[PDB]
Structure formats: structure tokens, C-alpha cells
Image (cartoon, coloured by chain):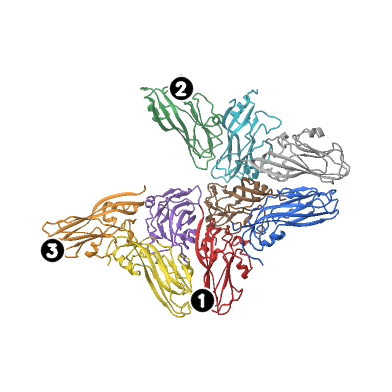
Chain colours: A orange, B yellow, C red, D purple, E brown, F blue, H cyan, I green
Amino acid sequence: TNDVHLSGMSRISQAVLPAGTGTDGYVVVDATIVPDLLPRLGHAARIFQRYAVETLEFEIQPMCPANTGGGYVAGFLPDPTDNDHTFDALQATRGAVVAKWWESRTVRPQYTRTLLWTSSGKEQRLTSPGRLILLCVGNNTDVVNVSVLCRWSVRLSVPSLEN
Amino acid sequence: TNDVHLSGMSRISQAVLPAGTGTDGYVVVDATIVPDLLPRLGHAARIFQRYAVETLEFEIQPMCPANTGGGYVAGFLPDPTDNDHTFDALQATRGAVVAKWWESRTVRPQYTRTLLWTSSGKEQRLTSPGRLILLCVGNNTDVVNVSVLCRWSVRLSVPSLEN
Amino acid sequence: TNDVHLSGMSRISQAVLPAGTGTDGYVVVDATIVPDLLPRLGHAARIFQRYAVETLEFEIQPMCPANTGGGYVAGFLPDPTDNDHTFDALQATRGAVVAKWWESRTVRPQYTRTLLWTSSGKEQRLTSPGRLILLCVGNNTDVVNVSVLCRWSVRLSVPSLEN
Amino acid sequence: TNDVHLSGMSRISQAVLPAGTGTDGYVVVDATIVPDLLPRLGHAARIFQRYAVETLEFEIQPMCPANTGGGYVAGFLPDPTDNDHTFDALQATRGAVVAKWWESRTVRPQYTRTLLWTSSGKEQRLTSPGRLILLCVGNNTDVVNVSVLCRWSVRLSVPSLEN
Amino acid sequence: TNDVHLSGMSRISQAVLPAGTGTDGYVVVDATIVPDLLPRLGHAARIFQRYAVETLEFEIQPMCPANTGGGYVAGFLPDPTDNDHTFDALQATRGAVVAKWWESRTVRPQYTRTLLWTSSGKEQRLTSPGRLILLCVGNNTDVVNVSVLCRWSVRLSVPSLEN
Amino acid sequence: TNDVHLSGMSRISQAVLPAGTGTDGYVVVDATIVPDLLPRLGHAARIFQRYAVETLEFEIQPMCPANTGGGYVAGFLPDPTDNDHTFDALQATRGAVVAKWWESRTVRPQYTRTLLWTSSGKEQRLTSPGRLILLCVGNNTDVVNVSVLCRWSVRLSVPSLEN
Amino acid sequence: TNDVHLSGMSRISQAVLPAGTGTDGYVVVDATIVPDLLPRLGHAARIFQRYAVETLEFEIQPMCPANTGGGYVAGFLPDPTDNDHTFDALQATRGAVVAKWWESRTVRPQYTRTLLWTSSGKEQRLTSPGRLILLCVGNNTDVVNVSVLCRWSVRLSVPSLEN
Amino acid sequence: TNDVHLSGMSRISQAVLPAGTGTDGYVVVDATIVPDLLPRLGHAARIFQRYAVETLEFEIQPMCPANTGGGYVAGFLPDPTDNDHTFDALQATRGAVVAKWWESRTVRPQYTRTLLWTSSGKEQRLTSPGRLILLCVGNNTDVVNVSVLCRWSVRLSVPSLEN
Amino acid sequence: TNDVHLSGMSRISQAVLPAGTGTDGYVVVDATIVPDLLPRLGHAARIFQRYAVETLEFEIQPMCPANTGGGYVAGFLPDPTDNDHTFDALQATRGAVVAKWWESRTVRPQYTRTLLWTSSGKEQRLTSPGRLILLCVGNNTDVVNVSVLCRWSVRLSVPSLEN
């Protein structure tokens, strides 16, 4: 077939949350998923022109001591468009997970599952499959170095070359 | 299957055309079809993120005496975008019906049949499957209290909670 | 195959018979059927050279109050050339219908079925499948605003680009 | 089927390159592909809302004499949005061909194959499948009268009338 | 069977186009296809009375030096009737070809495919299957001796003898 | 079958040829075959719009003494439009017969087999299948009262009423 | 197949034999069978180059009163070459018929059955299949207007064009 | 089988057409085909008595610069006996090709397929299968050195020895 | 099998025929095909004792402007021995090609097909399977740089070490 399947896993973001600064609803990560954000896919984005997302998961990897009065809710909402960053809105999505900050966790969302576009558009419903949000629950006793990782499997289409 | 199917019939609009105000080409109704317009699906759209239209039929239901020398043409054009509210243009669509103001009628269009978006978009041929237009033909002798109803059936897709 | 199939319904004419101006044998419509009379086929006849008539009906759709003392005969004579415009003459064609002015009605004729030509010619039995006539019967008590509609289904032949 | 299949071949543009005006990367033709450009599709686009491309080709037909020091690269890139008009951006596409100016040549691109819309819109990745670019390689000895032909096959879908 | 199949290939016309006299749109050949024009068929035309065209092709055979800044478009429009001799109108037909004057080329049109008449009629839609047009593109540097050839396959019917 | 099959045998003409007034080539009969010529069919022609011939035969019936130096040729040529009235022209038809004036003889032509119209038209190859010609051979020694009879089997197709 | 089958029936000759001028052995017709002599075949003779005779018959059609003391012998000898025009030599051939001058008659000969040539040769055994002779038997009382007719079926070969 | 098959390809002729001497209808080659003319068949002809052509093609091989405004029409007429050396006559034969003088070309005719004789006789349609003709179309600007080659496949039949 | 198969394509010769020196007969190449002329095979011959030629072809590859009045004949005689270097003699062999000097061409002969010998012979009918000849036809107008290439495939025989 003409379609090219790429897979990888990349750090979407890394936030450092100081000793006492989290509270119910504080947005610690808000990452809109674009090929530029996943470095290996960022390169293959310049070779093809449309990409379609075949599997997406986000691994929340917070790094703090086991004595942290932590808490987060992590979710992937499928519109890059909207800013509805509240707990209930995250928990309404499929992947949604909640955990104490000393607990790793994986969000397995359900998404567009459709053909997209490797470069910006007038209508951005076809340039990004969604965005990953990470919210505080309660308030952290200790310093947290959260890094979220996106594992991705993508099928790429129409050859091209954007310089 | 994940896709949730949902059906109903809703009053899209209700106009009161006064007692002589018609003439050929007068727009009494011009409703752009979106989840908020159909109050049951209104709520199903706050839950889910996308939706595809499985059936659409519009039931023109004017209410006036049998002694009304009226005339309407009713038609569903599938560009939620296109201002083109003229007899010929409406009659070119599929479901298009024409009738005296004391005759009920149903339009059965053909349409997008595609997958849309419960939330408003920057590009709006992904938000609405089109619009329903009721046009005067000749002039009414009498008052008409027109109510268009939409019978609909719809498959809603990715879970969410878009306030 | 090569052939294109188009289908639509279109207003062929509109007349506004006022107060008391019809009368046993008065001609309110006399429409020689060509692609130009059907807006959609007007455009698709510029593109193709020839066309064959696969279905043809006419839907008389007059508009008056139910207290109107009218009546019409309507029929399709299958000679674009035939000038005979009397009651018996119409009542000898197949679908021929007669009805009070407050009834809609459908004439379903039988016709050429042959392959014609989208463009004017020296012999016009190759340009038109016939002509739709609408006569008055009795003498209307009131103001009729009548529109006749042609429901067509046609197949187009050999490419071209007529100005 | 409710889908019509149409097929033609239309001149996309005509450029006349005078006796020494071309040069590595000089842009001679750059044409965003839309129904209006291809005469017969323009007339049928005025009749259906939607269209989808089944076959796309571009025949480059330069007219000049055999003693010309020519050269060209023809490519079709499939965003009507993209400006990258450099040799290596064209060669990166599937159809890309190069030739001396006294050599006709067909480009066989790979393209959208998706369902578009026959009128302009806010996002034009839905109105057009791409653009044909024609660039000079080297400078011409002589006068070139280049005409690019686009052969096409299209399937049109939802009835309408854009007067 | 009673039907008689004849085939051949004949010179429809021969134009001599002097050193500098062609320009965009100049009609160099305009030949209405009649049995008299194909000499072998011209004879068999006097034996039968109706002829029907089973295969038609035109071979454009321009004769000039390879250093000619030439260009032509050749097309077969299926009405002997109309004088629409513009490039776009020719290219709209099926056979349509364009080429530099030092390139042979074959137009393979689509035509009436119907029964015709071996002698003149009041309505000439049935005496000739169309006409072959040859137009200049750009302007010729040199003298061109174009000869167009029609290859034909015809089935002849009803015996007869016209003296 | 909606179609009506109708058959008769009627007198096309009657010519009385005095004692010496025939001569190689003299046209005694030249009849163009149309409904009205055939009595029964002339009435059935008023009821329907088209007819297609299904069998035709012309029975030549000269009455005169056995001592007559006569001679005729009779044939059916299939245009109503051909004035070729010469022996060789007649003989080259299929039906063609030659006989002495005291022999009954039957022309069995091959002919149109196509669908005509029951009404005169602008092109007359859609109204009559041909014409029966009768010419003298030698000269007649005696009075000859020739009568020709068309035998016909015809289908009639499209209901109507010509008054 | 490449072979073309033609059939017809033509007047080979017409002799007028005055009141008393025939006698045993008088040659009234002596016709060498060439394509030029059969008018329809005369035309097709210029299109092909070799013709082969598939069926031959001659219908003797003498026209005189029933009171004629007539008599003829008619025969087809298969060499165009030889002048042996005696009764016995005619009766030796296969078709040979004898009859009173007031009797029609048909000679059904046997012939070369071989490939021939549509135009003259140094050896004429291949340009004509034979010749038809008509001789007087006894002597005619009255004037006879004999016309002999050749019915022929021929298959034609190798395309060509003789002007 | 007592038949010896022989193949070859030989030069029938070579002509040098100087600077400006060609013109429509100028005969530059008129070669009647006999075994003496094909060198190897010449020798095999002396050994046998009868030969029959099984394949027969002519390769026209003109040599001149690409900058030549020439033109030729070549064909093979199948009688050695016919002098018709006009264009129309050549184009009517099967092989007949036309071409500018800087284009090579092959005539695949249709021909005798009969059994001929290796030696001269009174009738010469038994000794040659026909003759190759080459005609000018337009005037050559330049010097052409034209060689026509004949590829042949012949079957030789009755042994002898003609010293 | 014990056999070792070896293939290549080698430049047998490079001549350079100056701008007016060529004429019908002039020998430009005359290369006798020995293992040493084919360099790759040159080395394989020192390893084995004998070799049998399995596929042989010669590609004539003259370079010159397209405005050259040239002409050649190329052919492979399968006689290393024979000094017959004349047009007819070359045309008698199988591959033999003729062509203008600005046309590439491929001779494909039929040859010895036998087992020869990689070291010189006292009978040289077992060391080289023939020789490739190139002649002039007419005279060249421009300098010609001809290079002939021998495409070869070979099977080599019996192990050895011949200095």
C-alpha cells in the first residue's frame, strides 16, 4: 500500500510544580497535539502532507516523594478548539484518569480517528486530533516534576516536502 | 457498536405571516439546522462531541382557513452557508415541495450524510447539515400561522461534556 | 458506461388568472419543453450534445381558496409542433387530467422516449419531447395563482460546451 | 446510485514565454484547481453541491521549436493552500515530471480522493484538490507557447442551483 | 444480415499555411463530414440510402520542419449545424488534441452513433455525423502543409440508386 | 403492448392509359405513401401521433387485353424526397418488378422499419417511408386501366386527437 | 470478415425487335457481363479491386402480345471470350431456356464461381464471368420489346479507388 | 510440405529528391514488385516456378534533416497493371501512410494472397502482386534521400531452373 | 550445469565521420567480434577455453544534430572471414537496420549460435561469430560521432588460465 505507518513515544510536556502551588482546578499542562510536538513525527510531517491518527495514549509520569498530598486528573479532549478546562469536563472524556501525584497513570482516550493535515489550516479541526489537559486535585505538599508522554501510532499520506 | 442512535421530531420555527404580506419569493422561514434547534438533541449534543444525520424530513404545517389563496415552496439546501433563497434554487433541491397554504407537506431532502460537530466551528460545513427555507408563492388572502417541524434521526459519537 | 443520468423537478410556468377571466377553452399555459425550461438541465445541456427523456410528469399546482368555481384540463401533447389546443385534444393524451381549481393533480403522459438534441434544430421533433397545455374549464370565481411543475429524469449523451 | 460521473479534459492556462525570460525556478503556471477552471465541470458544479475527484492528470503541451534550450518541471501539489514553488518542492510530489521545452509530458499526481464542495468556503481544503505548478529549468532560447491541459474525472453528488 | 460494412481512410482536407499567417484561433480546417467527402464512401453512397457511422477517427498530419513554432488544436464537434469554432469549445469535445505543428496526432471522438442519410435533407441532423475543426495555437514560424485524414467504418442500409 | 397493430390493403392510385400514350420512362404513377392515401389508416392516423411500418407491398394491377405490347416497371424508393424517376433508379430498389401490361405483379420492397409521425412535418423523412413509382416500358398497343394497391401492416403508437 | 457481400438485379440490355425481323439464329442480345453493366455494382467496382461472383441468374422479360409467333433460346456461356452463338451451343449450357416470346423465363447458369478483377486485364478470363446470349427461334409475328435482367450476388475484395 | 518458405527485407528503390523539386502529386517512386527486385528472392525465383506472397510490408525510409517542410504519401496498389498515381488513389489502399519527410513509416497493405509465377507472361497479374508508389505532399525545403524497403515473406512452389 | 553465464554491453567502436565525407558505400565501422573487443569478457576469456554466444545485439548510437542529412545501414554478417561490405549484402542479413544519422537503432541478428574458442584459431570459423558493419547511405551534412555498442550474453566453457 501507499500508506506509511509510524510509531513512537514522546514527551509532550514537562511542568515543575513548586512546593505548595497547586489547587483544585489549577491547569498544570495544556498541550495541543500537533506533529511538531512529537519530535520524530515532527520530521516525518515535512515529508508527507496528511497524517491520520491510529493509536493515542498519554502516560502521566509525575515525579515526587511518596509523602506528597497530591492529586491530578488528566484527560484528552478531542477538539483542539475549546478551553473548557474543568474537572467534570475532563472526567467526561474516555481516557480520563485521576490519581495521587505519586502514582503513574495512563489515559487511553477515544478521538477523531480521522484523516488530518500535517500543516496549519483556516479550519483547525483537521490539523490536530485534540489536546491533553492535566489538572490539580487538592493541593500538593511537595515539589512535583510532572512529565506527560504521548505514545502514538500514525499513518502518513500524500508525499510532499515543506521547507 | 459505540455510536449512539437518537430520534425525534421537533418544531424548528413558527412564523405568523399576516393577512396580505406574502408575495413571490418572500422568506417566512429560514432555519439553519443545529443541535440547539431540536431541543431533545440540544441536550444530547452537550454530552457528545460529534454527530451524523441519519434521517431528515421537514413537515410544513401551516394553519389558516381553507379559503386562503396562498402558496408556499419549501426546501432544504445543504450549505449551512449559502444565502440563496429563491424559488428556483429551492426547487432544485430534492425534498422540495410546493403547495397551497392549507396543504401540509413533507420535504425529504438528500444532504451531507456526513459526520459533523456538536460544537460551533470556524468552518461551518462541519457544524450544520444545512438550512430549511420556506418561501411565499403568490400572496395570501388570510393570516397563516406556519410551524415547520423537523423529524430527525442521528448517530452521536465521541463522549464529552461541552458546557 | 458513458451516460449521465440527471433528475429533478422544476417550474415550467406561472400564471395569475384573476377574478373571472378563464373560460371553457381558455389557454393559461402552453409550454414547449426544452432543457432551458428546467433550470438544472439548462446548465447540463450546455455541457452535453444530446439527451434522452427517461421519465416525465407534470404536477399542476394551482393556488386558490377552496371557494373557487374553476376547473382546468391539463395534458401533454408529444409534438412540440402540434398547435391543436382544445379540451378533447388534451383529453386524448394519456395522463390528461381535469380537476377543480382547488385540486392539485398529476399528468403522467407517454412520449417520444427517443434520443433528442440539447440545442435548437431545423426540425424540432429532435429538440423537444412535446408540450404541456393548461386550459380552463368553466370560469373561475376567484384569483388562481397557478404553477406547473415538470418532474423529469433524463440521460445525457455526448460532450460539448455550447455558449 | 445518486452520483453522476463526469469526465473531460480542459485547458488550465496558457502562458507565452518570450525569447529569453525563463530561468531556474521562474514560475510560469500556478493554478489552483477548481470547477470553474475546467469549463464543463463549471457548468455541472452550478448544479450539484458536492464533487469528488476520481482521476486527475495534467498534460503539459509547450509549443515551441525543436531548437529551444528549454526545460520545465510540472508538479501538482495537493493543498490549494501551499505556496512552496521551488523545484524540490514539486519533485517531492508523485506526478512530478521534467522535460525540455520541445517535449510534451503528462503528470500523474496522487491527490485527495475525498468529498469537496463546488462553491468557495472558509476552509478551502474542501473546495479544491490542489494546484498545478509549472516552473522553468534553465532559460529558453526561443518563444514558448505553453498550454497545460488537465484531464479529469469527477463524481458529483448533492443537487442544487447556484444562480 | 442485410447490412453492409464499409471501412476506409481518406483525406478530408489539405491546407497550406504560409510562413507567418497563423494565430490563436485561426481556423485552418473546417470540414463537414459527408459521404461525398470520403471518396470510396462517396461511391457507395449512391448504392444505398441510409448510412450509419460505426467508427470515426481523424489523423492530423501536419508537414513542416521540426523548427516550427507551431501549435494546433483539433476537435470533432458532433453537429454539422453550429459554427462555435473557439479553442475551449473544441477542447470540450472528446477526441480533442493539441500539439506543436511538427507532431502528428489522432482525434478519437464520440459522435451521434446513430442512423443517418446518404443524401441531403430538410433537417441536416441526419445527413452528417459532425464536423472536424482544426485551429491554430500560437503562430507558425514556418510553412505548414497540413492534411487531415478521416479513418471511418460505416454500415450501409436500404438499397437504392441515385443518379 | 400499448401499441396497436393495424393492417389493410388500399388503392394508392388508378390511371387510365389511352391507346398509345405510354413510353419508355413515362411516369404513370408516383405516389408518396402517407396515412391519408390509405383510407382506413387515414382515420387511424387522426387518433395516434406516430406509426411505424411493419409490412409493405404494392400489388400492381393493370387491366387490359392480353394482346397488348405494353410493359411497366414498378418499385418502391424509400424517401418521400427523391425525384429520381428513371428505370435504372427504380430497378435498383428491392421490390422492383418489370412485367408486360397484361401481368399482375407484386413489389416487395425493403424499407424504413422505423417510427414516423402521423402528421406533416418540417423534415419529411419522419412522415413517409417512401414512394411507389410506375413507369412505362415500350409503348402500349391498347387502353390500359392500371390500378396500384398498397398492402400494409402498420403499428400506431401515441394516443392523441387531431380535429 | 474483410469480404463485402453485394446483391442486386439490373437490366443488362433492352432490344426492340420489329414486326417481322427475327429468324432462327438471329442474335437479339449479346451482353458480356462486366461490373460496369450492372449499375449498382458499377459503383462498388471503383471501391474494391477484385470481385467474385456468388450467384447469377438472368430473367428474360419479353414484352409483346399473346398473339406473337415468337420463340427464343437464352443461355449464359461462361467465357467472355468466344463468339459461338448458335442454338446448340447455347442449349449445351446449364441455364439454357427456350420459350415463346410471350413467356417470361429465367436462366440459372453455372459459371466460373471464381475470383475475378473489377477492371480490365491483358487476360480477360479474370475480368468477366461470361456473357448472356439471346437468340431467335422461328420468326416473330409482332413487335417484341425484350429486356433481360441480371440478378446477381457478389463478394468484393481488396479496398482500392479507381478514378 | 513441398513448399519452401523464404523471408527477407530488401531495398525496392532509392531516389534522391533535390533541394526544392517536390510538389503535390510528384511521383518519386513507382516500383512494381517482382522477384528480380528483391535480391535474395531473385535467386530463389530461378530455382522455382511459382511463388505466393504470405506477408508484405513497405518501410519508407527518408533521410533528410529534421528542418524539412516535406511530406509523402506511400501506398501499395495491388495490380501491377494500374497507373492511377494520384493521392486519393494511394490513400484508398490499406497500407497507405502519409508523413513529413523526416518521419519513417511502414505500409502494411492487403494484397493478392494468391499464387503467382516467377517468370514474365502475357497476363502480368499472374507475375506481380502489385506496385509500391511514393508521392510528394507539399514541397521539400531540403534534400531527401529516400529508400523504400520491402520486408517480404514468400512461399516458393514448383522446382525448375531458369538459366 | 557446469556452464558459467556472462553478460554485458560494450562499446565495439567509435568513429567520427567528418562533415561532408560520407557517401553510399563508405564503411564507417567494421568491427570483428572477438572476446577482446568486449572488455568484461576480455577478462573472462583468460579463465575459460571456449565460449558459446547465447544473445547478440548491436546498438548503433550516432551523435549529431537533428539537422543532419545522413543515413546508415548497419548489419551483422556471421562470417568473420568475408569481405562483402555493400548495401544489399548487409540488408540480406537478419537484424539489418537502416535509418537517418539522428536516429538510434538496434540490429538483432541471427548468427552462428555455436561453440567457439576464446583463444585464436587457425580456422577462425570457431573464434568469432561474425562482424558488425556500418555503411553510409547518402551523405552526411554534419559531423557525426558514431559509437556502436554490442549487447552480449555468453556461456563460457572449460576452466583454464590462458595468458
Quadrant of image for the N terminus of chain E: top right
The label nearer to you, 1 versus 3, is 1
Coordinates of residue F31 in the picture (x, y in percent): 74, 57
As shown in the figure, which amino acid type bears the numbered disc 2?
Answer: Leu
- Residue lying at the far left in this picture: please name it: A67
Coordinates of residue C132 in the picture (x, y in percent): 58, 67
Whether residue E26 sits left or right of residue A126 in the image: it is right
- Tell me the subunit letter for badge 1: C
Res I51 seen here: yes
Coordinates of residue F137 in the picture (x, y in percent): 80, 49
Q: Quadrant of residue H60?
A: top right
In the rendered image, which residue does mark 2 sit on?
I126
* Tag 2 secondary structure: helix
Q: Nearer the viewer, residue D137 or H4?
A: H4
As shown in the figure, which amino acid type bears the numbered disc 1?
Answer: Cys
Q: Local crowd at mark 3 within 10 Å, few (<14), some, or many (≥20)?
A: few
Q: Nearer the viewer, residue B69 or H89?
A: B69
Res H85 seen here: no
Q: Nearer the viewer, residue H120 or C149?
A: C149
Whether residue B159 sits left or right of residue B152 in the image: it is left
As shown in the figure, which amino acid type bears the numbered disc 3?
Answer: Gly
Asked whether the residues under marks 2 and 3 belong to the same chain, the reply is: no
The correct choice, above or below, for H145 with respect to A111 in the image is above
In the rendered image, which residue does mark 1 sit on?
C64
In the rendered image, which residue does mark 3 sit on?
A20
Q: Local crowd at mark 2 within 10 Å, few (<14), some, or many (≥20)?
A: many
- Tell me the subunit letter for badge 2: I
